[PDB]
Amino acid sequence: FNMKLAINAKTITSGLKYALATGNWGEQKKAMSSRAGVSQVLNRYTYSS
Amino acid sequence: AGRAALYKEVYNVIASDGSYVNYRHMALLVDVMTTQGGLTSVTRHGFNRSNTGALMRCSFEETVEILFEAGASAELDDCRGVSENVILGQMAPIGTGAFDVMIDEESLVKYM
Amino acid sequence: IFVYQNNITPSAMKLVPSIPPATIETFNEAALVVNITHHELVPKHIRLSSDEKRELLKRYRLKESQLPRIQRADPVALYLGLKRGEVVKIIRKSETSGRYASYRICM
Amino acid sequence: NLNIVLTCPECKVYPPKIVERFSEGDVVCALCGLVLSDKLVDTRSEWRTFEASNPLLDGNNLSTRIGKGETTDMRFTKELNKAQGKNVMDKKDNEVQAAFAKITMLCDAAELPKIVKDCAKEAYKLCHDEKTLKGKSMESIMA
Amino acid sequence: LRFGEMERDCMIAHGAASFLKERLMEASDAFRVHICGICGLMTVIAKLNHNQFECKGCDNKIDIYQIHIPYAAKLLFQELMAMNITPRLYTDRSRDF
Amino acid sequence: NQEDSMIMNQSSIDRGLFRSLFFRSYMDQEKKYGMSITETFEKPQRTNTLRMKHGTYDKLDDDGLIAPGVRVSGEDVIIGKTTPISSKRDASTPLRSTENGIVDQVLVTTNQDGLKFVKVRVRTTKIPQIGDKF
Amino acid sequence: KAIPKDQRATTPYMTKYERARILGTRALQISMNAPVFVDLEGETDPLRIAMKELAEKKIPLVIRRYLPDGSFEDWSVEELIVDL
Amino acid sequence: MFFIKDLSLNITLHPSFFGPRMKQYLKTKLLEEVEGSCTGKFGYILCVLDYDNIDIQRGRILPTDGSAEFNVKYRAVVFKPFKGEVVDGTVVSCSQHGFEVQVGPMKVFVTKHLMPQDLTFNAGSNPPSYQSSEDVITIKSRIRVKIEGCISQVSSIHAIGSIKEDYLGAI
Amino acid sequence: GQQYSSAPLRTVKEVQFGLFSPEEVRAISVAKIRFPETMDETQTRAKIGGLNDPRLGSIDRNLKCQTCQEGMNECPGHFGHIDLAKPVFHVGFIAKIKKVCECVCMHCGKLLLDEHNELMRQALAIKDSKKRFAAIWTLCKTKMVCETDVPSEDDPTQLVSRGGCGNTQPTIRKDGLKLVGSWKKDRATGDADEPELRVLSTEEILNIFKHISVKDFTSLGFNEVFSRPEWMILTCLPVPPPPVRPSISFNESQRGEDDLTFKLADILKANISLETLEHNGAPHHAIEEAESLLQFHVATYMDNDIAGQPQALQKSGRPVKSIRARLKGKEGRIRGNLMGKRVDFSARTVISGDPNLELDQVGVPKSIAKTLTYPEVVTPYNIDRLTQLVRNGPNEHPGAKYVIRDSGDRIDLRYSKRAGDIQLQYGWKVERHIMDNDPVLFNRQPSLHKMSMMAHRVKVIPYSTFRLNLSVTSPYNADFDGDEMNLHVPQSEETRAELSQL
Ligand SMILES: [Mg+2]
Ligand SMILES: [Zn+2]
Ligand SMILES: [Zn+2]
Ligand SMILES: [Zn+2]
């Protein structure tokens, strides 16, 4: 029972990276209904913005 | 009386907002809903389900479910609607295109 | 015409179209208490003759399809005992022309 | 025989670039200064995620996998997930697919890079075919 | 820019029949097909160069016409066909009224 | 100044009233398409490169980038790229046609997996004009 | 079927649409180097030429006025009243 | 065969021609378009008959454009060949494959195989001929052919024909 | 341009809708379509004699389009066919098919009611093709027996014989793409209690439909020429050409196929599978299992948004764009490519007011005027002027962009080596810049008014905004808080007249 073969790191790593990036808060590249726009690019027009 | 009440009602909605629309406009709408013999609604159900052309009906709301039925009923669109000629990219039979223009060789040879 | 108080059994109603060319009409006494034709909103309907109709269609280059239609069951179509094919000439007042004549064919 | 050309016609040069233009299009020669068609084909405007597909082994299609909240799959999910699970038995469906799925599991676990991590798995699919003294062990050519 | 539905309406209201035709054809979409006179379909193998016409299946090398329609309609028609529906296009009438 | 429009002191505008800096950043990757096909950063030659941009490529140094400080303009080529397939098609990045300015800074890097990619900053100064909202 | 001249009943006056279309058509033809039926008193714009031809009723065109049934009444531009 | 057919052609005349020599130009353009013409439906439209009485009718002015359109009703002599028609003609070309026969406006070709067995190709002659035990068929010879079938080809009609059957061949 | 064809130019006067007879689908088709493979003659760069261009349409800037040639900007693209292993329902009719079965005898193919029933002869009388079918159904649905003898048109004692067959009619209900019947039965006068429960095969429904009398089916909606009911069930599949489902070849390891090309390949694969099953030892229940897979792929291809059924999905989790869905919405082919479309000779910018413009004029920015063009015909009247704008060229304001020769080919004044020494000829067209006093369509969207689109006189001016007279603000419903407006340029003397005159 080789440990490195057992636990797939990419599962949680890219699983969070997907949500945060795209914004479809759910698993994963097969998302719907998933809630899009949960994560979005921070407005940097003005400081108040 | 259905027509007269229907106009009265339409007129009120406009005049309540303190607006004026000339009679004829409201009259026409009221008449169109009427002519069939009852109260034909300005909905996918009412007008859009009449004997007009199939492409015309399909340009509003029911599109594909109208063209399948158009197929199995072997409909024939006489292309008199404005919708049809627009889909077809031809000069519509409206104002400027409501008549035809011909050269007369008689009058042509008369002026020279 | 048969003016009935409350009802006419479906047994009796089956004898209505049994004796043609003669025609039978059923009117519930309760409807007739008030003459609808007398109402503000109810304009003059006039039944046209076979010749008058023929002329209408000739004068406007019409097929019966192209005419506005009065429904057979219409309160006024009933009052006038209009038959399918029969045409009415409606004479209404106009805020536009004073008097406007429209026509309706029976359903 | 397929011959495709944009030769100006008036002053054949055989042949030169005619411009892609910026707005007008049609590639008018800087020679006869005429036209050729109307273009009307924007290649920059490819199908995004919003349909495009980048297949590396054969041709990808897909089936079923229903999940749209309209009417519940329940009975029908199992009707179709079983029915598509029967079909992946007709003509040696297993082999390439098993190899590429087991491939993405062994690499992901050691965190191998996708850009070239996937590149070598294309090499395996070229090595699994052809019959040159493989003495194939599955694990061996995987290394 | 988009000369959309509501803009079509204004043109129809104005009675600008030819201005509309232009917007929808010359100014956009406009395309030319060859159709068959028997089955009003876009079937015609126009080898317009050798001046050969043919609508095999009709065996019609004679009764053929050309029409100017918006390519999206040529598309729409091909689409309706793929879906087993026949939008037969005829250059003459048969109904009157 | 009727119907929500306003009049500006053109004299004040000259003195710096409401001017602003503007920086846009263009990016590009040198992608690797499998075992053999690799995009390249270089100045494309029009004889062996297909579908070139009508814009000019002269402002490119032989590494395929404009050096920072050069003034650019519409349709001009900031980043030269080719996607070899056979000799090679043109995959270059031109400046937006509706804009212009001077290149502010240009940086070269590799990413998480080590794909060469380059970021180009372009600076303009936007001086209050007519349809400008306030 | 075509209504006889003696039985024509449409307006003796030219419609806005008719006039706009005649002017459009003549101007188009004039612009495609068609023969001009009037003295161009220095005129160069084909619409201003068209206007001039219609002003003197020297336009050799006829309006085929279709009726909803399919029949029609033909009217000469020379004979149509231009009160517009 | 060779028919007289009543036909009509729509012509679209530009306003510049709305002068007195209008009918003259119409009758002319008609002849340019129709005469010489070869259709599948009607065959070769050879000669327009009764010039002096060509019915021009009233030309309808085409609305957005200036031009008038007339349906010029006329009458002409046509030649429409048929399968089964026996025709007389002069040989034109002759090769190892057969020989073409000119029948008025059209050429009818006879295959080496659609002739009797006795008639054989002779390359060693000026011009190349077909030789029977009794007959000799070459470029000037007159032949009676049975049309086997026609092909409506653009601006012409061509046909295949036999001289194998009884009462056919050289004349 | 687009080359000349000797074919007569005509206008479309009537559109005759109908269904495709499989005979016709086969007859039109220019290719068999045998393989779910796109192109790639196994790792190659040419189309496979199997799916897209087996003999079919042409793409990729290459003529090869089966003798037809021409290539892309002329070829409409011609259809292929696919021969289906077993009949399948066309998803759209599925219900009209059901209703037709409900009206006719599922054994002899004869109308359950006729001239003998009074209510029937009455409904049969209905002139409207749809209303009569509607009425015929509500009557015939209820009838669960094909009658041999019915009471005479006078006496109910001596029953007159109509058509034969005594068979009991099933109670049909749909089980999504499948039609299943429930036959009333008899067994000791009662039964059902527990009836005969069987699914009606496409083939059996097809056969009954084939036997429906021309007079009978004509009383139902159907037309003997253009739409026989037998043509609703799909037996042959018209395959659309690449134009309807474009492909794109990016970079030798990237290639994009259209969702339809995917959906087709599934239909094919499912077909090839079921064909092998029937040919081999037919395991009955393993075949009908493969049939209702084929049924799904064909059905989901025309419509993917089906109620009750699972959607066909495309790897990325997104559902396949069916044909229905391309026509459907606003942004569909109808609402968004035909009834409204984007156009050339259009221009848009921020509007601003001007007390110095005349009511009917419009301030046009120099740049906008220098882009928008009017095609003017070279004529004795304009020849000299036009030659000057040509000389002026594309960069100077009153200049020109193109010269259109009689020959059809376009001269680009921006690049032509002869842009200087260009000598005009009567009849040529000079595509010149928009100039002061040209009529142009000005519009402010929404456009709920005829006054929301009005014709203005051009006035070329500096600065990037469209300037309008203040009193013309109200009809458009514009202000200068950041509003933009649309400008359309007529291209014909006719079109211009329309604007200026109406
Ligand atoms: Mg505003
Ligand atoms: Zn055909
Ligand atoms: Zn083709
Ligand atoms: Zn029966």
Image: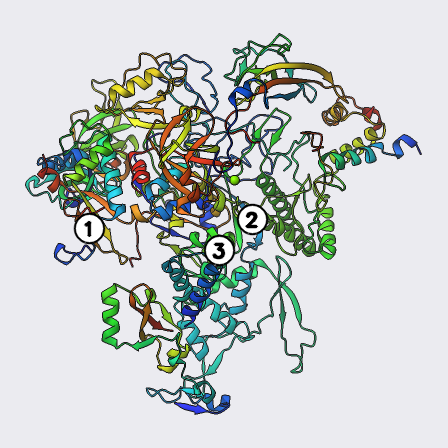
What is the secondary structure assignment of the residue under circle 3? helix
Q: Position of residue F106 (x, y in %)?
A: 67, 14
Which kind of residue does numbered mark 3 sit on? Ile
Residue behind label 3 places its C-beta within 8 angstroms of ligand 2: no
What is the secondary structure assignment of the residue under circle 2? helix
Q: Nearer the viewer, residue B70 or C32?
A: C32
- With C75 as the anchor, is F43 left or right in this view? right
Residue G31 visible (yes or no): yes
Q: Quadrant of residue I424?
A: top left
Residue behind label 1 places its C-beta within 8 angstroms of ligand 1: no
Q: Nearer the viewer, residue I11 or I361?
A: I361
The residue at 16%/31% (across/down) is G35
Q: Nearer the viewer, mark 2 or mark 3?
A: 3
The residue at 60%/32% (across/down) is I256
> Is disc 2 on the same chain as disc 1?
no
Dot 3 corresponds to which residue?
A: B66
Dot 1 corresponds to which residue?
A: G13
Which kind of residue does numbered mark 1 sit on? Tyr
Q: Residue furthest right?
A: A1
Q: Chain of mark 1?
A: G
Q: Chain of mark 3?
A: B
Q: Position of residue C56 (x, y in %)?
A: 25, 69
Which kind of residue does numbered mark 2 sit on? Met
